[PDB]
Image (cartoon, rainbow, N blue to C red; front, side):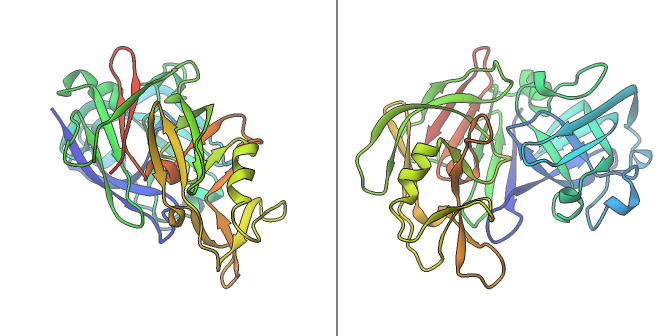
Amino acid sequence: STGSATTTPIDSLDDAYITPVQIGTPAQTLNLDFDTGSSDLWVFSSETTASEVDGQTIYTPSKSTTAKLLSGATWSISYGDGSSSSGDVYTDTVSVGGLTVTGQAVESAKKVSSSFTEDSTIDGLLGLAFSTLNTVSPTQQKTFFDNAKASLDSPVFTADLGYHAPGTYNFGFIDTTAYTGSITYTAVSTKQGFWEWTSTGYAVGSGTFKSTSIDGIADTGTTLLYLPATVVSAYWAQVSGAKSSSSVGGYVFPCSATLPSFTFGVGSARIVIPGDYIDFGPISTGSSSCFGGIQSSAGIGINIFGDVALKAAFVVFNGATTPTLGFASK
């Protein structure tokens, strides 16, 4: 089997991407944030505290003839941005782009933190990291990809995120029309539960490539590119007037600037992030200070190849017995 679904930016900045997902019988379609940095499929629901729902579409398990309470199971998750959610668990039929999993754990939110409530466009998350990170207790649950894998034509999914435009998540096949050149594959460590890999270096604009190993994660659920402070300083030093602002929470730059590109290495190959992809617009409405799309990872503990980086590439998440990642230009 295969599946193919369009993923759409939630706003004009590409702050996140939503992909429609069919849950239950008859289908209830929710727009989920596909997140290769986590491993829970959770949804706003009829059980979510009413004051914490503000415009999201909810899953109502009582209206699904295939929903079954997973007795005794609870979940609770906290994300790197400080947001969180928790609740109980159903199993139900879940379909993405024509690919159907029966018995998928659908984690129903009883509580969500303010940032989720305040984002009316995201009805939940669909985790695509390794199932070892799934938070369901006392019986850990598998991700949608893990459940689908054996049925797929090939045990892979691909992320093709657009810049200020829709893109595609495919399951079970590699669309050879969706990229240019060849796909360069690179090793993955699953030891932290992530799609963790090592970039071979970077360049700023037309500058020379610096060969240096940068361990990080391919994370579709993180907006920006978070890299070591040395690398980030070298980037922003090429933008007149750019500075790190403790009050704003990162590098800002004059909105009048033209940003240089940023290149990262994948083995001997190179992915170029155009300068425009690094512009996240005014820090507040009407400001002439703009927020940068490359930020320091120093306070995180891990480097994160988020959407800013991934949207410059066609990305293969290869879930073979020994997982690997593939990157191609597009």
